[PDB]
Length: 292
Length: 300
Ligand SMILES: *CCC(=O)Nc1cc(Nc2nccc(-n3cc(CN(C)C)c(-c4ccccc4)n3)n2)c(OC)cc1N1CCOCC1
Image (cartoon, rainbow over all chains, first blue to last red; front, side, top):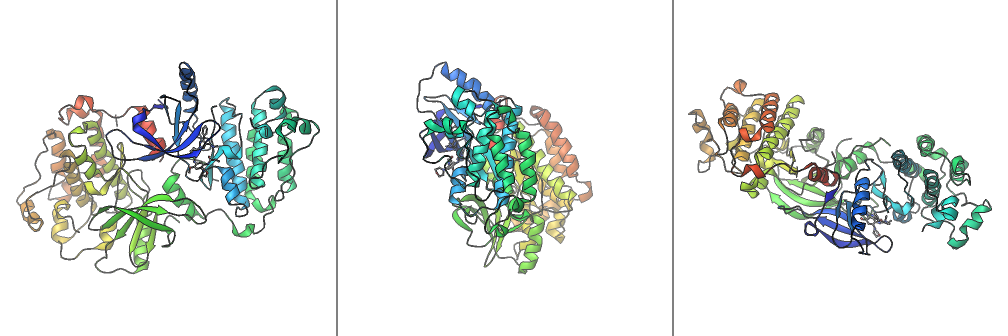
């Protein structure tokens, strides 16, 4: 009952958002039957059609993705099993956090970055609590509902520069491997969208990791935050932090954001007032969540 | 804190949506600072008010309109006080309930009709608990967020715009005390509530059609009211009549209309005789969960 079974004639793709990988992502419009309203949605299309009973196992997984109830994880709203599987979800009009942090290269205060790290861990801890592994966490796979509210997408289904060493050498994906990717994601945000291990061929990443070489300390990060990232990339998967621990740790820093992130001009980049925050929420973020 | 002050440079009107005596509503675009995104909103540009009011006073009542917090009353979000008075609210693509029921005329089931009455009574009870009086409750002033969720709009717009010698004043909706002596209480809002139900039960009929508005006061003193809508059992029509009693204290309370319409909504076909009603049921949980995740994140 959480997965609406669409038909082709009650929606339509409007403009491509992203393409290549999974398939294509479109800006879309939902046209209810009998009504003259057009509701903007997002549609995920798989380019390869090849589906018979492949569609049934997709529907089985689609019901699981339709059940993720969390303010910081995206829910699958509906499916259209036409030609090529079509997934329907809410449109996040601000785009992904990678493009967002890149456009606002040096116009992002320390309160936003730390809160984003808190909100991403809450969504991941939620998934771990549901015994689900994301396998592909990355700043590109986090969406900006509003600047104060991010959500993890691409849950369902090779980012070598994002995977734990055990996932590279042995294709072992756990929740502790997701912690590794979460540590690369944090680094992506702190460096404002820099490419991890830039230029370096992905085929040689397992070699440089076995030598204990890790991503460098981002300029705006105090040692407290970089040590967090370093512990996420420990060879021993069990030594890596738990997502529940990361929620508490980053939250403490979000209480004193300037003590853990050194940003030029940070004194004039604060989180919105209650006023802007009631305004945002009343328009596009009327959903129940946790105070930031 | 609940009312955002907007500058003319961070929003722009796109297209008109509909015009009324309080003003015209436009499909708007909010451009947040330093963002490349356009956020759709709804903008009401108000018509000039009689007893022209100072911007401190208008703002002093915009804070009251921005304070209503109920799933069934629309909250004013922002304001722009310049050469005109522009109100900003959440865009409701479905429109107002009056246009909706005329438009799906003989396609609406009794379970929707009785639920809309509960929801309107719930918004009105909230406004009475807050000691607020709406003064212009009507089917045109109820907005459809989703087909299963309606909200009262335009609260407080009558008090701050006033009126000239057009007594913009909804005569065929006001209690007799309001037409005669301009008395607006919670019990006269019950009078407009009865008329609002009658508009719903008739699928958008014009009340007192053919009777000039200047003559409503007198026919009301002769005991003449609105006729029984054809789909109404005497159960519902009794409740409507009680909303039109000359003694405002004999009229039903909103707290009572909530319970009474909840009762009928649990057995909707006992109370509304609609041809073909045995195929016009509510949406499934699936279709309902879909509407909520897309447009509505905020009695069977
Ligand atoms: C970072 C890339 C990106 O997503 N940009 C983006 C996002 C959105 N809003 C949006 N709403 C709902 C769903 C999505 N979305 C994106 C993707 C693929 N991304 C994460 C790499 C998926 C997806 C889900 C499941 C499976 C596979 C893919 N869902 N995105 C935009 O709407 C405003 C616009 C943009 N971009 C703006 C500038 O660049 C092009 C589009």
